[PDB]
Image (cartoon, rainbow, N blue to C red; front, side):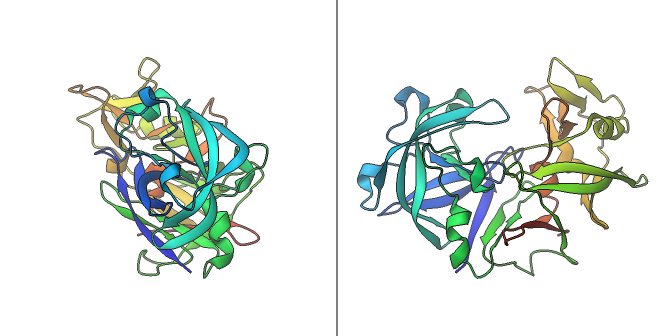
Length: 330
């Protein structure tokens, strides 16, 4: 089997991407944030605290003939940005882009933090990291990809995120028309439950490439590119007037600037992030100070190849017995 679904930016900055997901019978379609940095499929639901729902579409298990309470199971998750959610668990039929999993754990939110409530466009998350990170207790549950894997034509999914445009998540096949040149594959460590890999270095604009190992995670659920302070300083030093602002919470730059590109290494291959992808616009409405899309990972504890980086590539998440990651230009 295979599946193919379009993923769409939630706003003009590509702050996140939503992908329609069919849950239950008859289908209830919710728009979920596919997150390769976590491993819970959770949804706004009929059980969510009413005051914490503001415009989201909810899953109502009582209206699904295939929903079953997973008795005794609870979940609770906290994300790197400080947001969180928790609740109980149903199993139900879940389909993405024509690919169907029966008996998928659908985690129903009883509580969500303010950032979720305030984002009316995201109806939940669909985790695509390794199932060892799944938070369901006392019986850990599998991700949608893990459940689907054995049925897939090939045990892979791909992320093809757009810049200010829709893109695609495919399951079970590699679309050879979706990228240019060849795909370069690189080793993954699953020790922390992430799609963790080591970049071979970087360049700033037309500058020379610096060979240096940068361990980090491929994370579709993180907006920006978070790299070591040395790397980030070298990037922003090439933008007149750019500075790190503790009051704003990162690097800012004059909105009048033309940003240089940023290149990262994948083995002997190179992925180029155009300067425009690094512009996240005014820090507040009408400001001439703009927020940067490359930020320091210092104090996160891990480097994160978020959407800024991933959207410059066609990315293969290879879930074979020994997982690997592939990157191509596009």
